[PDB]
Amino acid sequence: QIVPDAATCPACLAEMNTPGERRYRYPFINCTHCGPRFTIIRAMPYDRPFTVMAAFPLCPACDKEYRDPLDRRFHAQPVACPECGPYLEWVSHGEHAEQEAALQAAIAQLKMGNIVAIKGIGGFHLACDARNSNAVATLRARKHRPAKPLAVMLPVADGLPDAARQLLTTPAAPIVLVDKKYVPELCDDIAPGLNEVGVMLPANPLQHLLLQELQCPLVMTSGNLSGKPPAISNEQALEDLQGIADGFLIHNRDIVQRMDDSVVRESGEMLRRSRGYVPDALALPPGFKNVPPVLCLGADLKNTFCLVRGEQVVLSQHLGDLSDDGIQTQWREALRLMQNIYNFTPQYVVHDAHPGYVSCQWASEMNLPTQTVLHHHAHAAACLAEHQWPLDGGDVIALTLDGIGMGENGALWGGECLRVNYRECEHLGGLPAVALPGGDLAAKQPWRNLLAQCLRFVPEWQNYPETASVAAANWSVLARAIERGINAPLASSCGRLFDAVAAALGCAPATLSYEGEAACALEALAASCDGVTHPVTMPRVDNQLDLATFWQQWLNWQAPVNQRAWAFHDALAQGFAALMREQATMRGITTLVFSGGVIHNRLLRARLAHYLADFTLLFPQSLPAGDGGLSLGQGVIAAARWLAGEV
Ligand SMILES: [Mg+2]
Ligand SMILES: [Zn+2]
Ligand SMILES: [Zn+2]
Ligand SMILES: [Zn+2]
């Protein structure tokens, strides 16, 4: 069996720190229990000749250890020592070094407040002293990332809550989001405007050597260019990162598979499932058996694919935005190895119903029967599958909250109440559909969504101080485009409503630098409020939330910004709760499901659970609520349709 890439174990770490050991300070020490796996395999079977390590014949001392059945390194496929293995290389503007000297050059650069690219297990990181305001601002400037929070590597987990330390020290070694109050050493440009910081521990020998030396937190963020796939080869690292990194700590062991760090909350909630979890298979729910080989393509953002067969499913690592330049190479290499590992040949392909998706174009190149699944049906089903809801388990009422997905008859959904089972999705109601002014621009500039909401729902909107910058523009050109349906499609998007409220509070920049930045900012603001008595509501009118009443009460309820943010989350949760209660009770449904990327909002979860104590509630935990779990949903739905003998 192949197991996920694993953090250096205590025994290899001790061997590495023991003077006189042959592997003393060797940055590529591994044994049968730890080290790279999925990332160094060319083809099956798992055997040194079919791994990146075939290039390095073993010295006799190594080979004796590889061959002794009682030795920790028995059949350690990528075992090596300094005599026979890979070695470090340092590259920096006409300066070069190797081995221990390569390591010391990188350490001296980091200590001086410089930024170094470091080769890891599944790609390259950019690093610098996370206490150094100057270094962190220079990294943000060079990478054009003014806001998006940076992951930080700490030497140890001391001082973090027990739940965080437990997750941080598993073989998977994820990034764990922890309250920033636990880590005062971090300069304030690490996650500005947010309440959490992603911390990780050293999990490969090179990282242990660095942190043992530096004894301070290091920014350890992905080594890529925005809009491009991460580098996995030295040449592509050297090329992509030359404007950013002051020097490069690289080496000559190949990485064959892109594998980003996994990201979880301290609570155990999965955000990004990659290194340490891939390629572990998951058991399908009861009633799923003898399923034919199905390839599920997932969706266009935060992509994962899924292989479904028998009574199991296996998800790929995070592969990013499928629209990015040359991402198909990494996607394809990941598909090849995963199919090789599981001896899998698909008979069917399932993909999203949006005909404009890249993933849909890729499906048509495959020469297999294809089928389509609505985006929000798949979110809801991934959450049912994760909770082991049986094939014949019965209908639930689902709340699927995200930015935008294609719904029935070409509609753009993102804030819907649905009656759902593994075969059917019936739309019951939700947010009103509101123009996205400027189409793709509506996700980047929150004021567009505020304008769209004001035009539809807020009489005399120009008189409110919340709308001043909008009001002062020549917004009437945009208003005219909106009336005429020119690049202004209607969407009932929960994410765009967050954006509209964030625009009205002024709590993100006018143009955003990353997807979801305004919603994250609004939630961080709301979470500093412990709850407040307020008059803001979102009544139910038929089967939609009445935003006219909402805006009138919210815009006229003066209070500190945190309390206004809180009141929005509370009113939205109460209004959706009332919709779901009526829908579920009158159909005799006792179980509710919640899914979509907006459901990663902790305040909204907590408020929903508060108003829906009379129901059994299913939220995602071991898979991402967002598009990272979508392939799974597609897979259980295709399986359930086949199992029913559907045509
Ligand atoms: Mg602390
Ligand atoms: Zn080990
Ligand atoms: Zn050796
Ligand atoms: Zn989605």
Image (cartoon, helix red, strand yellow):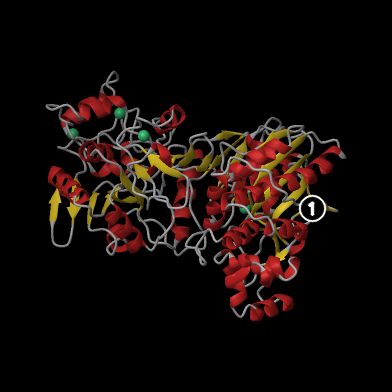
Ligand 1, image quadrant it occupies? top left
User: Are there few (<14), some (14-19), or many (20+) residues within 10 Å of tag 1?
Assistant: many
The residue closer to the viewer here, 404 or 542, is 542
* Residue at which label 1 appears: 429
Q: How many marks?
A: 1
In the image, taking residue 597 as reference, residue 170 lies left or right, namely left
Residue at screen point 52% across, 40% down: 270
In the image, taking residue 101 as reference, residue 529 lies left or right, namely right
The residue closer to the viewer here, 104 or 96, is 104
For the N terminus, give its image quadrant.
top left
With respect to residue 194, does 79 lie above or below?
above
* View extreme (front): residue: 558
Residue at screen point 30% across, 42% down: 217
Q: Position of residue 555 (x, y in %)?
A: 68, 60
Residue at screen point 42% across, 41% down: 180
Q: Position of residue 54 (x, y in %)?
A: 27, 42
In the image, taking residue 374 as reference, residue 164 lies left or right, namely left
